[PDB]
Image (cartoon, rainbow, N blue to C red):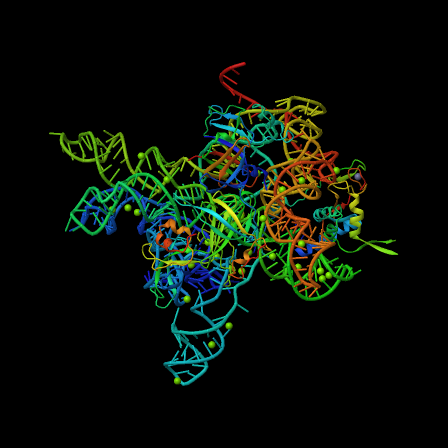
Amino acid sequence: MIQQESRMKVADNSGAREVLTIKVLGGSGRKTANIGDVVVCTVKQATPGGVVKKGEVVKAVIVRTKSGARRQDGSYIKFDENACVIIRDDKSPRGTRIFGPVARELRENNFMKIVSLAPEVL
Amino acid sequence: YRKLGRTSSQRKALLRDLATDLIVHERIETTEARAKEIRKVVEKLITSGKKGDLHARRQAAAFIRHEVVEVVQVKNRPVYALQKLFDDVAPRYAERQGGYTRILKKGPRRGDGAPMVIIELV
Amino acid sequence: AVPFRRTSKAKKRKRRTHVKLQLPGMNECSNCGEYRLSHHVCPECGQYDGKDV
Amino acid sequence: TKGILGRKVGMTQVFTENGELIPVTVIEAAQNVVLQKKTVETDGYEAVQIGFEDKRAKLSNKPEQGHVAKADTTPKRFIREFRDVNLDEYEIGAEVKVDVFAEGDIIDATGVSKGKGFQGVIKRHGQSRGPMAHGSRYHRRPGSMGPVAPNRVFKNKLLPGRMGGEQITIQNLEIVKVDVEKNVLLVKGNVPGAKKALVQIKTATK
Amino acid sequence: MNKLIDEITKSQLNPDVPSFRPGDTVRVHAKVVEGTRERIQLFEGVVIKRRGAGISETFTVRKISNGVGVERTFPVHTPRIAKLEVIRRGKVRRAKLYYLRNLRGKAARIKEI
RNA sequence: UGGCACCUCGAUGUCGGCUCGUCGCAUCCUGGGGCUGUAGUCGGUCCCAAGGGUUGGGCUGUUCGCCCAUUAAAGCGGCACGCGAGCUGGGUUCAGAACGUCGUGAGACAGUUCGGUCCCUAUCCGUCGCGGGCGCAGGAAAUUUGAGAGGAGCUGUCCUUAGUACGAGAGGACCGGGAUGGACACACCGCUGGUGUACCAGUUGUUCCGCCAGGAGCAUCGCUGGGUAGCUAUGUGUGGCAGGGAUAAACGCUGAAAGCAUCUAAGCGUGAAGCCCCCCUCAAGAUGAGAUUUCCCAUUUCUUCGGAAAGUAAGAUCCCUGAAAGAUGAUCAGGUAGAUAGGUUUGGAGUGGAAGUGUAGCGAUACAUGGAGCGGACAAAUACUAAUCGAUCGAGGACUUAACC
Ligand SMILES: [Mg+2]
Ligand SMILES: [Mg+2]
Ligand SMILES: [Mg+2]
Ligand SMILES: [Mg+2]
Ligand SMILES: [Mg+2]
Ligand SMILES: [Mg+2]
Ligand SMILES: [Mg+2]
Ligand SMILES: [Mg+2]
Ligand SMILES: [Mg+2]
Ligand SMILES: [Mg+2]
Ligand SMILES: [Mg+2]
Ligand SMILES: [Mg+2]
Ligand SMILES: [Mg+2]
Ligand SMILES: [Mg+2]
Ligand SMILES: [Mg+2]
Ligand SMILES: [Mg+2]
Ligand SMILES: [Mg+2]
Ligand SMILES: [Mg+2]
Ligand SMILES: [Mg+2]
Ligand SMILES: [Mg+2]
Ligand SMILES: [Mg+2]
Ligand SMILES: [Mg+2]
Ligand SMILES: [Mg+2]
Ligand SMILES: [Mg+2]
Ligand SMILES: [Mg+2]
Ligand SMILES: [Mg+2]
Ligand SMILES: [Mg+2]
Ligand SMILES: [Mg+2]
Ligand SMILES: [Mg+2]
Ligand SMILES: [Mg+2]
Ligand SMILES: [Mg+2]
Ligand SMILES: [Mg+2]
Ligand SMILES: [Zn+2]
C-alpha cells in the first residue's frame, strides 16, 4: 500500500538512493499501489556522481512491499522493506544491477529485464 | 456474561463476596439479575470441592474470602470458609451432577422497586 | 427549543392516552386461597409449589 | 429452473483440481416436500409451494395440520414459493433432493441479513466524519438537511435508524460440491444471514 | 467447532505432513508452477506462527535473504507442497515468535535441542 | 457592475472552508446523427440527448488565479451569492500596542502589522425508524398477486481482425470477438490483519493470606508478549450481463395534391448511455381495504323491535427460561407432549510446559513425572436446577337482485 508522500528505498545501481512518491497511475481516483505497479516519483537523495541527479522527476516500479501480494494458491509473501526500481518509458531499468530479492509478481507484468538481473525471485 | 452496573475491578470483588455468603449462610437475599450471576460461580466452586486435590484447593482458595464461619471447641479452633466448602458442602453433593442452587422469586423492594429473590443451596 | 404556542386541553389529554399502567398478573393460591402473583413465592402462607420454602 | 430451501451451516474452504483454494458455504437441505401447485385457472399465476423442516406436533396447530394432510406429510416449519418454474414435474408430495443441481451450476441465494440495532449515519449510510481536532465539534453527525427556501426537509434525507434485517439476494454465485448422502450443498462465496438462517436457492435468472 | 464441516473436509486433510512447532527450521519443497512448467523451489527458514484449526491451519516461515527479511505463509494441507522437512528443532518460550521481525543476526539465534 | 428605496432597526448573523445534497441545460466525458478546407489517424461546427460520471497536491484568509502530477472528463449556473437553534473562526467589524502619512491638538486612514468570550433541555409541521387502536358485514393459521413507489444506470487499457481498407510516403482505422482494471454498491468472517477490561503467560514496588512454598489487593486493564466468541476493512464473494416495445435528431420505401418530382398529406421501415420494460427492494389503510389452501361451527338468558350479555370452539395472550433479535414495545427459539437458559461429562480454539515430589548444582536456575495445567462468549450428549400452578380474551355470521340449486 503505497500512496502520495510515501518514501521507499531504491534497489538498483542508478544514482538515486531515496524516492518520494508523487502520484499513482491507473485511474482517476486511485489512491494505493502495490507490487508490480508503476508510480511517478521524485528523488530526495542521491549518491555523488550518479546518473540520476537529486531533484529529478522519474517513473518507477515497486518490487517489494511491507505488505506483499497473495497468490491464487492461497499462499502469501511479505518483505521487511519497501523498495523501488527506476525504469525508462519502456520496461527497461535505468540502472545496471538490481539488489535484494524480488517478488515473482513482476514476472507476470513483462518486467523480464528486472527479473533476470535480480539475485533471486521469490 | 453480564455487567452489574460497576467496573471490572468492583464486579470481581462483588462476585467473591456473594459467593462466600451463600457458602457460609446457605440462604441469602439478592436482586434477580444479581442472583443469576453467582449461580454460575458457586456451582463451579462446588466442583472444585468434589475433586479434593491440593491443586483444586489452591485454585478455589484464590476466590473464597477469609473469614471464620464459626468457632469449634475442639482448645479453640476457628473454622474458615474454605474448610466448610471442602469438608461439609462438597460431600453433600457427591451424587448430584449439576444444579446445587435454586432461585425463588419474592417481589419488589420498597425503596427502588428492585425484584428480590431467594437463592438457596440445595 | 422553546414552545411556540401553548398546548390545549384536547392535545394535552390525547397525548396521555398511553400514559396508563397495566393490571398486575395476579392469581389464586390453592392452599391459602388468596390472591398471588404467578411464578412467585406466596408471601403470607409462605410457600411455593406446596413446599413451604 | 429449479429451487430448494436450506439452512446456513457455516463457512470453510476447499482445494480445487487445479490446485487453487476457494471459500465455500455449507447448506443443509433435508426434508423438502412439494405441498401445493398453483395454476392460472385457480390463482392466475404459476408457482410451487415447498416445505423445508418438520416440527413436533405440539408446535403445529389445527389449521396447518389439514393443509399438509393433503400431501400426506408431517407439519413443516418453513414454507415458500417458487415462480417461473416448470410444472410438468413436481407431483404433490414428492421429495425434492439436492441432486437436482450439479457441478458448476449458477444459482441465486436469497436470505435475511444479520441484524444491527439503532445505527448512526456513518455506519448505516457510509457518510463522512467531520474533523476530529482543530477545535471542531462536528464528529459523527448527519449534515445539513437542505436549503432554506422549501421551508421543509425533502424525502430521502438519510438519517439514523434500525440497520439490518432486510431481504437481500446475491446473483451469479457458483456451486462447488454437491452431496446426496449428507444432503449438503457447497456454494462458493457468501450468503446473507447468520448461522442456522433460512437460505432459498434458485437457478440464476440471468 | 462444527461437526458437519468436519466430515465434508475430512478427505482433503494431507496425512504426510510431519509434526513441527513454531521455532524450528524447516525446508519447504514448494512447487512453483508457471504457465506450462512445474519446478520445485526450496524455501528454508524458521517457523514463526501456526494458527487455525482443521484444513484452515496455516504456518509462516521466515528467511533472511540478501540482507532483506522475507516471510512466507502456506496452508498446512495444500497439495502444492511436494514434501516438508524439519532440519533442526529449536527451543523457544513463545507460541508466536513476532519478536524476530526487528532483530538482526547474532541476536536472532535460536538454540537447539 | 448599477438605478429605486417597496418588507425587516421591540435584531432577517455577514466572507471562505467542512458535512449533506437537490434542480436547470445555454453539454466537460460517455450515446445517436447532418456538414466539412471529411483520403487514413487526429479534428472543427451544428442538431437530439440531463442516465451516470466529473482528481490529488505547492503559494495565499482567500472566491479566483498561477504552478507540479494525473484523468474518458477535470462543465456553467439556481436553491437568503443553498446549508453557523449542523461545525470552524483564518478574514471582515469593539476595547491594547506599533509603523508610514494627515492634523497645532484630542485623533484619523476600506493603508499595514501582533493579540483578541460564537448562548439555547425541540412545543407544532417536516425527515428517519419502531409500536398501540379500529377498520376491511362470522371468528382464525399460513402462502401470495400487484396498482403505486424507491435503488441501480459510470468507464479505461491490452490482444486479434491487421500493418488489412486508405495513402506515394510518413503514417494508419470503423464495424466484431477476447482478456483484465479504476471508482462505486450489497453481503460475509473461511483466508490476511484490527479490537477483544470475567482467556493464558512474564515482570517491578508495596500491603495482605501467621511463616517457606503457593496466591490475592492497588498502582491507566500497573506494565509487557499473545488471543476465543462477537463487531470489523485495508480482506473475500458478487453486481451494473445479454436483451424487448415505442420514440428524438436523422436516413429511407410507396405515393398524390400538381399526369413529372418530393420521406408526408393517408400508410409503412430502420433509428440514442435517453422513455416504458428486463434486474433488486417496499408495497391491500390500494377505506377501490384483493386472491388461494386449511380449521371451528350454528349454544344459553332476555327481548315489543332494532338487538342486548355470557359461558365457549378453532386460535391467541398474560406469566416464566432466553437469543440468531433488540433503546422500550415488537421479532424469533421454548414452557415437563421439554434440550430454552444455567450446571455436569466429553471435546475445540488460545496460551504455552501447572501445583506437589524427585534429580544436578554452594547459589540464581535447569531437567523429569507431562503438548502438562488452565481454558468468557464455540460444539455434542445429559432433566441435575429454573420454565410449577392458573387466568384472560376470542363466532353463531344484515338486506336486495341474478344464476344455479
Ligand atoms: Mg493497504
Ligand atoms: Mg485496577
Ligand atoms: Mg415470507
Ligand atoms: Mg470533539
Ligand atoms: Mg494452536
Ligand atoms: Mg420580534
Ligand atoms: Mg439542448
Ligand atoms: Mg458524438
Ligand atoms: Mg461530427
Ligand atoms: Mg447527464
Ligand atoms: Mg511545505
Ligand atoms: Mg443574489
Ligand atoms: Mg450564502
Ligand atoms: Mg440555519
Ligand atoms: Mg486603540
Ligand atoms: Mg506633525
Ligand atoms: Mg496569545
Ligand atoms: Mg440539541
Ligand atoms: Mg398496525
Ligand atoms: Mg476475520
Ligand atoms: Mg513467600
Ligand atoms: Mg488495598
Ligand atoms: Mg494486554
Ligand atoms: Mg446493458
Ligand atoms: Mg425498434
Ligand atoms: Mg384479505
Ligand atoms: Mg447459544
Ligand atoms: Mg409461545
Ligand atoms: Mg444446556
Ligand atoms: Mg516444570
Ligand atoms: Mg542440590
Ligand atoms: Mg418445579
Ligand atoms: Zn398461599
Q: Nearer the viewer, residue F317 or D47?
A: D47
* Residue positioned 43% across, 34% down in the render: D205
What is the x, y in percent for residue F231? 55, 48
Q: Is residue D192 visible?
A: yes
Q: Nearer the viewer, residue D23 or D81?
A: D23
Quarter occupied by residue F313: top right
* Residue positioned 49% across, 63% down in the render: D134
Q: Nearer the viewer, residue A29 or C4?
A: A29
Against D96, residue D18 (above or below) is below
Q: Is residue B1 visible?
A: no
**How many discs appear?**
0
What is the x, y in percent for residue F69? 35, 59
Against F105, residue A102 (above or below) is above
Q: Nearer the viewer, residue F404 or E102?
A: E102
Quarter occupied by residue D51: top right
What is the x, y in percent for residue D132? 51, 60
Against A53, residue F236 (above or below) is above
What is the x, y in percent for residue C51? 80, 39
Name the quadrant of the C terminus of chain E: bottom right
Name the quadrant of the N terminus of chain E: top right
